[PDB]
Length: 127
View 1 (tube, rainbow, N blue to C red):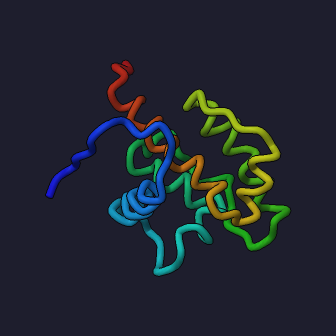
View 2 (view 1 turned 60 degrees about the vertical axis):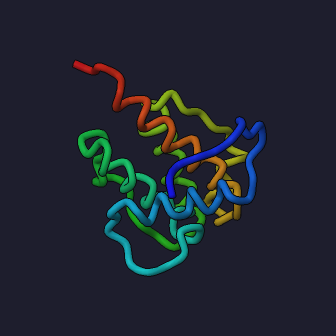
């Protein structure tokens, strides 16, 4: 069909999730076959999504993929003052802790708005 929706949804429905789950797949990301909620948690995956829109912004030189919470959080923390910051995006530690802990819905609550922001930069007439 087509992108159609009657009335403005004040809250987020269960459908919204799916739409966000598909959007990711659509984008050509250098990643194998595996859940998106289990990967994103890592963090290094988020920096990739941006690369598509803004490759320059991303560096992918400091961040390192690991399998330990310690590193996980350590990585996110920076991405908050290295990436988010640029996107005038801010988030408390309490929220992050959950993200790194591969928490369902938590990290997603940031993915929805995350994309909305990126676009905000596209339109912006940056010189």
